Amino acid sequence: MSLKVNILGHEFSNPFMNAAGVLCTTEEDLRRMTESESGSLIGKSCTLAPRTGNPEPRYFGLPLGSINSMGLPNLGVDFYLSYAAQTHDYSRKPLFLSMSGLSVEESVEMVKKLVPITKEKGTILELNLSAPPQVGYDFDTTRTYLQKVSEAYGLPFGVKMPPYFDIAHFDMAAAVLNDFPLVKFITCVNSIGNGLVIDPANETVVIKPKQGFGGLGGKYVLPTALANVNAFFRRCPDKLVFGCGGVYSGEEAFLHILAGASMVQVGTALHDEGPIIFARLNKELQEIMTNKGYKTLDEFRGRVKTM
Amino acid sequence: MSLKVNILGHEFSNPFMNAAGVLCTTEEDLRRMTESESGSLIGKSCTLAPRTGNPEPRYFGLPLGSINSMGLPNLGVDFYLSYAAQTHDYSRKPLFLSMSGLSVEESVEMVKKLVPITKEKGTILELNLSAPPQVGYDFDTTRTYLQKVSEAYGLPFGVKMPPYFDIAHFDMAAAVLNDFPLVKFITCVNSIGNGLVIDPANETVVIKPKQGFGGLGGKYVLPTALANVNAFFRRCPDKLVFGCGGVYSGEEAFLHILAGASMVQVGTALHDEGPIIFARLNKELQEIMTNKGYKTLDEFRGRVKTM
Ligand SMILES: Cc1cc2nc3c(=O)[nH]c(=O)nc-3n(C[C@H](O)[C@H](O)[C@H](O)COP(=O)(O)O)c2cc1C
Ligand SMILES: Cc1cc2nc3c(=O)[nH]c(=O)nc-3n(C[C@H](O)[C@H](O)[C@H](O)COP(=O)(O)O)c2cc1C
Ligand SMILES: O=C(O)c1cc(=O)[nH]c(=O)[nH]1
Ligand SMILES: O=C(O)c1cc(=O)[nH]c(=O)[nH]1
Image (cartoon, rainbow over all chains, first blue to last red; front, side, top):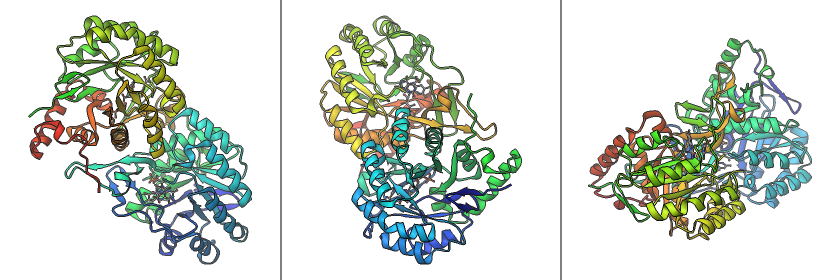
């Protein structure tokens, strides 16, 4: 069977990639992702200038997933642009970059710098609209960001969206996104935002920033992610959907693809296991496809049955 | 040692009650709740006329909790009002009624009928603003509901709120809530809405309504529930917060109370175990308290520690 995905002119060996934020902040991280069995990789959501991020502790591994308030620690746009122009081996896998300016102006200035590298190297942009006020939760601000970034970048790009939990919100988000033809992929989803974990032994929160409030990832998010994937697969047929959330196995990948996902992103589980996970995910998805008699992902993508 | 709670002019033997929707639709359900070791009970979110709800399957138990699209099945407001006025034994425990009119006008008519019974029996109102755009996700609609209900009911009442996932949303919700002094309790939280569960074997969704989309309950929602409880505990200090989400043990109950919860509601776990859980929860909470040297709930309520 084939795990290949053919999108934006590129051939991906498999649908699997890292979720933005995990094993993607430094050059060592990026080499490790490139040397992995992953089909692609994405860089840490970057800012115009370097950020060191939030105070410690800011990450807590849970039995059911993860909580985090990292604070967008990143080496700055110039670092990721340089990796994309001079360091990355595009013969290994295609490269994506996440940009998370804390204002539309910052995002425009960054996006402008990427244009020449995309043209020469094929580096794909994922605009983050779900950085912990979340842009995805204001449909007016979202339109402004897509307007301004579409004009500045002038090239195909995608968007990391916050999870929606309302059918009307799926509709309202789809209506904005469908007014922007340069948005070719929608990544669903970012962390379930602003959760609180408390340790019963010390009666204390487990992360220092934001009084313990942090984004939830892992097993807590699979149902939410699958829903967002399917809702945007159906409402945005002129676009691709990338799945992110709750993937620990080939089974969860299969479910993401069945819901409509082209690429599948792994976060918490990759934070837990390391890049060796990509080799397990390829093997498990292959086994599932072999058992169901699917020869390509295209035979079942978005083909989830309803009653 | 005491698990007692003095709120809303009442004494509650303990903080535990059922979550609206679970063991509260029929009189048999309400008798079993009154006969339980629970401190209170709440009736099913009712509509002006009776409803049979959605087609089957409409509920699916999961390893990590529940997915549901019940469709607000209820025997009509007249039935719940009759239970509150004639059947319910107030010497056993205080009674709550959940009202979920699908319009402002419907809710107004329903709450107007409650006024005389609240005056005579003490029946307490929880207004559902989180029934499957969900009212709580539209702050202008929410203000209207609150304005009209305050006008028509004219007595202290409570609100069932949807889970929020954004700091600005917490602030915006509280701002609306803090303009209505008749709102004395905020129940956080209703289901994490519009999730999607797919069975990998049959490639099919597990609930029939809404193409498989339903509200999530159980272990999936605890960190979200704790966050909303604490956020409204801090932002709405002239009000009480009720905790709802992910309670399967005394541990989860302790955590909710530490975050600010006066009453703790139990849904998915009650569906799984039956009304006996109230006896286990009472015992497990006392155990934790004995092990921590606590005699009353007031010694730890809202005393979650930050760093
Ligand atoms: C430590 C950490 C850092 C993250 N950083 C980013 C980030 O920079 N940009 C982003 O768009 N998402 C970021 N995320 C969110 C993940 O990409 C992903 O959307 C979320 O964790 C859900 O996927 P999972 O269930 O596989 O973890 C981060 C998550 C974690 C745990
Ligand atoms: C079968 C079922 C029916 C529910 N019906 C209602 C309802 O009528 N009104 C309501 O406000 N919440 C309703 N809920 C939500 C619960 O009250 C609760 O907010 C949610 O299940 C999260 O708590 P849990 O983690 O204990 O399940 C329902 C939940 C379930 C599982
Ligand atoms: O860097 C972070 O804090 C971060 C960014 C983002 O978009 N999502 C997340 O969960 N964390
Ligand atoms: O009856 C239902 O469908 C229902 C109502 C509500 O408020 N919440 C929920 O999860 N289900």
